[PDB]
Length: 83
Image (cartoon, rainbow, N blue to C red; front, side, top):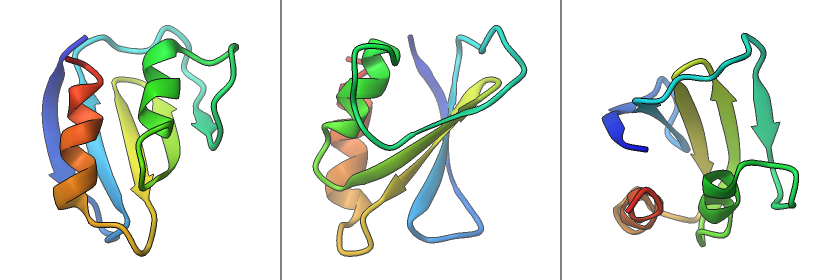
């Protein structure tokens, strides 16, 4: 899986990351905690210090960081997940 685009969102604690592989279903999913049912890359992102939640729908995931955290330190670890 590869990141094709990283952008800024109308909000500060959230960024829209567009992936190459699109979602099969048309529904969305919001993951706030890790567990065996979610996709693996999804649990790896949540384990990143500073990640608050993840909105996943279509061909992108919107990651929300902690109000006290900064993207300069979170974003790299987030992209590191896709290796």
